[PDB]
Length: 10
Length: 253
Ligand SMILES: C[C@@H]1C[C@H]2[C@@H]3CCC4=CC(=O)C=C[C@]4(C)[C@@]3(F)[C@@H](O)C[C@]2(C)[C@@]1(O)C(=O)CO
Image (tube, rainbow over all chains, first blue to last red; front, top):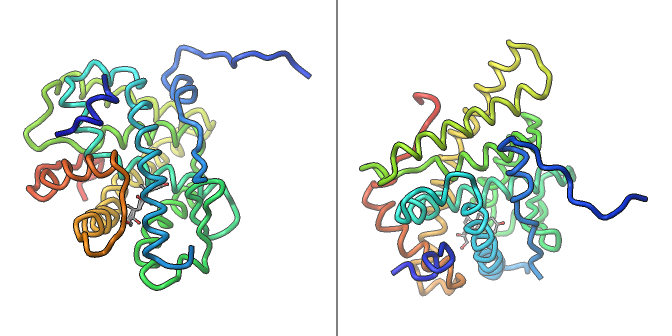
């Protein structure tokens, strides 16, 4: 769903 | 002539805000439809920089991951619009929106058909920073507060920590004001004024998101958004439209 935001935040 | 060296960090939140603040992005048109797409493409890059910035803010990464994602989704437009107001205010060259050093929108372009109604809201921030003569330190504190200004109605998973973090930056804004060396009475008045300006950002943002969401959704309008922005907006809308976004206010209103 929020793969990009999640990736950036990890 | 001095040697190469990094400036001295001190044990204060504002000294850290200053070091972690991203550098201004360069963008790298006389039709509103084209201008809009260009602004969005810049915006997506500025938002990626903003996510990296938020992860450096003392306390942020200690919040539950869902909390972090929600705060960013709820506040990105506010952070982007406030920074746009700042760059425009610091240009001191009149009513001009300074999206990037190589992308300025002057009075002539701001009045193109379809542009004024959206540019006027962005310009409002600039004229307010100018009217209050906001200092860089005050601006950094206020900008951090915008990241912590819109929450889910049901509360965050890390609510207690969030409340502590928020109070930390409210005090830091107070320290930035005090530092200007006004008297006690001026300090009280200024805290009132800057918190009123923070509250007024909620209304500004409501005007901007209206354009953001409609232009994003109406695929027939052929206004493009980069991937990152598209994903955020896609997730934000449901929360926004369901009335889940609670605006924290300093003043009753
Ligand atoms: C009126 C809205 C608010 C506009 C945004 C206001 C905040 C901002 C500041 C910037 O430095 C770069 C992009 C953004 C983040 C923006 F300017 C572009 O995205 C286009 C934007 C969404 C808008 O013009 C659009 O809806 C056009 O599609």
